[PDB]
Structure formats: structure tokens, C-alpha cells
Length: 178
Ligand SMILES: [Zn+2]
Ligand SMILES: [Zn+2]
Ligand SMILES: [Zn+2]
Image (tube, rainbow, N blue to C red; front, side):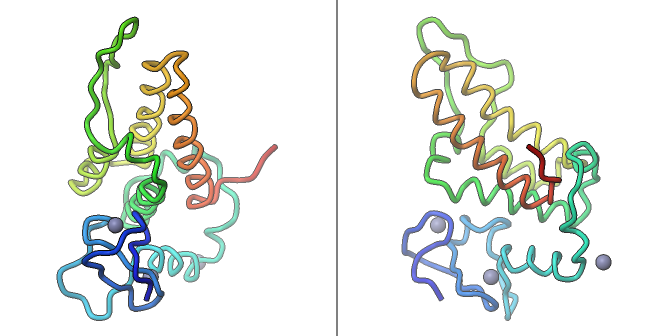
């Protein structure tokens, strides 16, 4: 197994996957690494199994159909994995915890949103459709762009949104277009 966390790239108290060489901090994995379970398979492994059991699940989909899916166990897992893929980028630090807004010439958003809030909401089964999860994720970046206006820091929101969107298209097998 790897000797660093797959998500944050640090050493520490690591739980090792039984079916691949990845390792995780307890609360870096999503869902948090399960208490018992021998063997244990990480979220990467669980996603690969879904694909392997239903190869057709990789054929292209329309985003509008994906968003309307109910949050059954496989879609819950896919949104957990997509969230985890965003935490895998170090620039997610800027969006992880609760923001505050006091900048001359700007007003804070009406509905603040942040990664750990989405993480709690997934853990608490608060989303009934994929759309709920995706709307909160996109809101994070939209709030950031609007607040930071012409400051170059706006680019951090573009960068992390790009990571989200590329992973969304991969994980939910969105039909490729120009
Ligand atoms: Zn970690
Ligand atoms: Zn694994
Ligand atoms: Zn099948």
C-alpha cells in the first residue's frame, strides 16, 4: 500500500485498501473509513465494481437525465466519489470550511456553501436527487466568482470548478461533445 493519503498526500494514521494500493486518513475517505470490515475496499474500488458489473453504465448520458436520478445507493456513492475527487485537489482548501464575507465593494452571497457542508449533507442523506448535490457544488464556485469580482483570486473558483466538472462528466459518463 501507499504510505501517504490518496486525498491530502500526507502521512499519518492511514487505513489501507484491501483491493488496491491506496491508503486514507479516516475522515479524508468519503464515506469516513468504516469501523470494522475485513477486507475493506475503498471508494475507488467500489466505483470500479459498479462499472464492471454494468459495462453499459459507461455509455454516454445526458446531464439532464443524470440530475433527475434519485439518490439510490449507487448514485449516493457516485456523488461521494465526485466530492472526494474535489478534495483531492489542494486548492479545495479554499472551499472546505465556512466562508465569511467582508470586502469593500462586494456583498456576500445569499446562500453560502462550502465542501464540508456538502459532505455533512451527503452523510445525513439530505439529497433526494443527484441535482441537489450538483446544485450545491456549483453554488460554491458561483458564489466565489460573484464575490471576488475582478480580483485575480476569482481564478481559484474557476480552477476548482473545472476539477469538479471534469470529474462529474467522467463519473456519470456524460456524453462527450464539442
Ligand atoms: Zn488525508
Ligand atoms: Zn481501493
Ligand atoms: Zn448490466
